[PDB]
Length: 114
Length: 115
Length: 88
Image (spheres, rainbow over the protein chains, first blue to last red):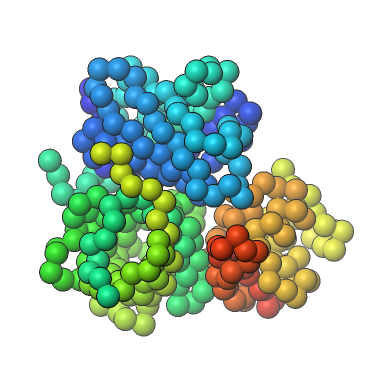
């Protein structure tokens, strides 16, 4: 159905085989999260694919996609569900040959509900 | 000299315990809500808007020990006042019900929220 | 995977974090992320986590940890100094 509000840990692996770990938080249609070198935000327009903006705050550590500016990721809705496990294929906007595979694991609901 | 409600957004945090155990994480502030996590734990709290913030800490990765070496859920107390600075914050956060157990948190603002 | 410095060649069997700690002890100096990644041919994400994990194994490793200005490049980084290691 529709993805659960709460806190998720994510694992991601790119086509250039770099991998990394982060957290992700969903609060309604708002998606936010980050890892050791970059952070991300997006809104669920709930009718399209989700555009996720990736911002680098630590350039001493390379992007798993080895992009050294801000970029956008495409996440398709089709695969999002209310399960406690999720697997996602997310490519760079305007370049399908560049991508990350995400495994999301649900940890906990949110403290103030809806 | 400013109250704990300061900029909404995403923060990177570095923390060191009283026994010099450490970690790296991110933290998101959104209205009266605090959420974040690292490689082994997640944390949440409500800004009661008059008191100290109670922050609930839960470990999800049992391959890695808690930075305070606590083997169940615990709570941290985050002080009302925070004192501020330019995109930098340093916080003393002790464990609820035991003040000798604590973490020093170094937080850096990354970005506002998209909405 | 990782390489083992000639400094500690004769410890092949020990887990990575013991191996790193022992190497650190042999430097007698404040070690950062970049020092470690260099010497063990691992990437930086991995190097960071190793420091984090070591700092949580106090029954094995006796150390200190400061968070300090470098550069700069007006930032601070975690550095670690490892007193010694217990293998019994």
